[PDB]
Length: 316
Ligand SMILES: [Ca+2]
Ligand SMILES: [Ca+2]
Image 1 (cartoon, rainbow, N blue to C red):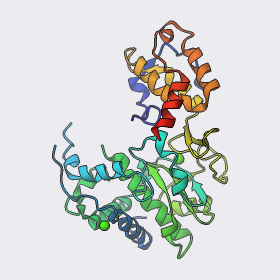
Image 2 (cartoon, rainbow, N blue to C red):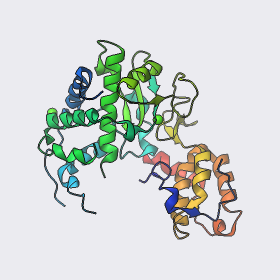
Image 3 (cartoon, rainbow, N blue to C red):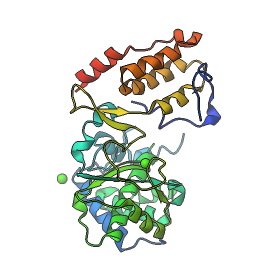
């Protein structure tokens, strides 16, 4: 599985596609709170019994030698134990997320995540690695102070715990159920957590937190308005217990207007149809109708809705 929009390359490596005009495009050291956050998180990772062993086979691939098994673990176990979605199949994993979350959801975005991360956060990251067995290859982290999504997601787990602890004294982290993919995060708790208050705490650690998904105000987050990896959560009409990961056409329309080479348009458009069909038939067909309003589009293999839908059902 590849993430077309989320892992979209930079515009530097892109050129206009044949569909360019067919669519439009308009806090210094580790403190008492982090320490406890480490404690709680490291504990959870232990329940996984990740293999402390090195790996059995672009130079910086020595780190794939050091943390190869760690990465493999998160990849094999995306969820609330890892607190990571890195490596999930949105088509299947979306039906599980709701079942793994506590009743009250809370989310928010970061501004300049990677840039705003103080050195302390990395020290904390090391401590987590010490407690789960990789403490001898801890120096490999200074190379940031393949696995960026992993480590950044782990730092996000430390942040949320820390902020919760500093905002509400004595809170029990055992009831925190979150999932991260880099700096994007979906989270929950049995009681309403106010993200606007977490943000105030984030300031103390040099973090800039803002309402999620471009919002002027921190509003209540719900399954009807929450997004994860830019996708919404929409239950199927025939099987409500099956959740469609719904990427907005708006995001798709923009992506189809570019490409790396005209020789990948076929693959790239395939990717986009795999995301696109979840919006519903009427939507998908209009989408293909447009693609086919230009010569190259009419020469592309585009999967018809029903086959995609039926295949999806059978995938469960
Ligand atoms: Ca065990
Ligand atoms: Ca986000």
